[PDB]
Length: 130
Length: 22
Length: 77
Picture 1 (cartoon, rainbow over the protein chains, first blue to last red):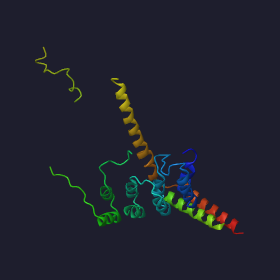
Picture 2: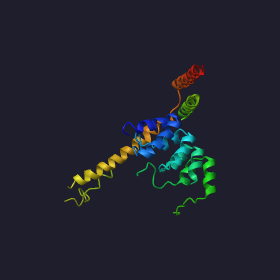
Picture 3: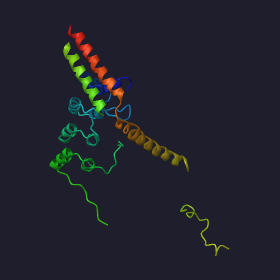
Picture 4: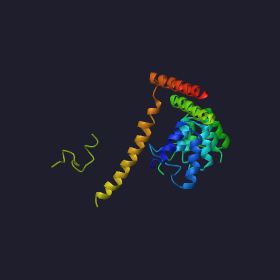
């Protein structure tokens, strides 16, 4: 924050690339801000890039090892294929503790994610009949 | 969402062109 | 109707009729904070980004394109 993270968030959301990168490896050495602040509405810069589906920023952020959190879940909800395409290979949240990637993936019929996660291999739990 | 994505893509193309102009 | 019965008030058919809360406030406030956070994040934000388009969006898109045109033309020469 401190009118230091505000520029970072604005650059990320507006679509800039060079400025965002420069901010990354500047704050990486001056230890001035945290890369993973959530100012406005609990929105990590990663989430901001996710919801604008801007692939370049997301793939750049994966380089700097910024904390991921349950961003995979947000991408799944948003139905963006490239985001989960990248994320797949390598406190209190707003998602119920029950939900796993496959459950939410099935909650929205979108062939691609179901096929991908089946390729990786999962196993949805089964209930006990009554 | 479509509004956001269109406007953001245009803005990114603007920034790239301006950066590579000079 | 149900809540009419939950107390030890009647408990008989008519024939046979004759600190303590600072800690509670402490935890209750945390619960309230969690609920209001979840609500603000999950409805007044998340459901706003689900509304149909209007003529404002047309204006803004076309104007932004025009501005980018003017800037590029100005910096070409």
